[PDB]
Length: 83
Image (cartoon, rainbow, N blue to C red):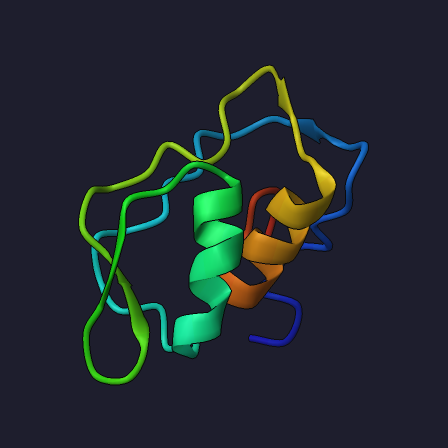
């Protein structure tokens, strides 16, 4: 894989049903500000921010926001395509 993470960019429409899994994101506890920015229930696991409830971050027909795009980019999740 190379471009597994699709270019999540604010302004683009959300075609897929992206879900932020209830699992440690690998991100530092600081990123919980972004998770909470997208109204996400968060708890710190291993010095990393973890998700407690599977988040319906993107919805087919929604519109990827700024901190939202950033969130998905930090999550290393592909809200579009992976090639």
